[PDB]
Image: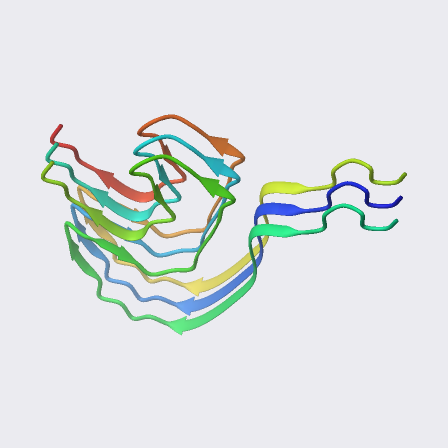
Length: 64
Length: 64
Length: 64
């Protein structure tokens, strides 16, 4: 009766490897979003109306 | 009666490898989104109306 | 009756490795968001309406 229960991985980010030698960036930003990098987001549950989950480089401008 | 239960991987991101030598970027952004990088998003559940999940380089402008 | 219960990993970020040699950045930002770095976000639950979870490089300007 071994492992009668779970042995799982839910919403998992592992063994992410990155090797970026050079980024000679002249980044000019005027009222905007710029994303230059490793972004790991692991979630199990997100709920609600109008909800944003794991947004990267986002620009939200509502005339509401 | 081994492994009578689960041994699973649900919503998993693993063994992602990246090797980017050079990006001599002259990134000019005026009121917008730019994304230059590794983005790993692992989720199990997202719910709700009007919900955004795992958005990357997003621009939302509503006249509502 | 071994492991009758859980042995799990829920909302986990592990074994993230990054090697970035040089970023000779001339980052100019005027009223905006810039993100240059390792960002690991592990969550199990986020709830609510209008909620933002794990936002990176975000710009929110509402005319509401």
